[PDB]
Length: 109
Image (cartoon, rainbow, N blue to C red; front, side):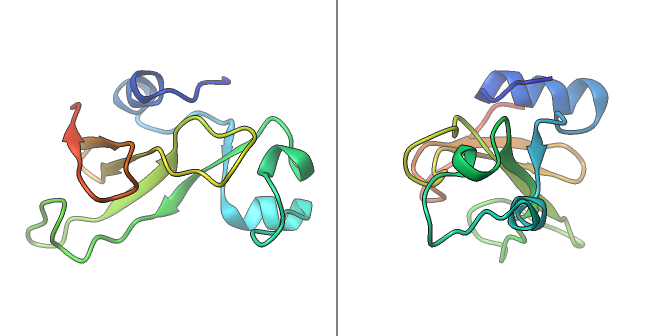
């Protein structure tokens, strides 16, 4: 509904098999007039964070076999600098969190 914590978003994933609806995509923010070069999101598109955008994984930091796909979503980002604390989950719903922007992950699963 308006959830944006590590446990909270992870819960929503596990439960409903989707993100919460408070996370729009980059494209949507951009349509609303957000610019990445410019300041924080909420300014231009309030009540919103980024999520549901692709993480890809080049098969290194998170596991991948056959062709496991990955998507990322913001954690705790209303105002300030751009999201960095983040959470990434796989298609088959193996979940990992980070505070360090994709240096090191930890499973929450």
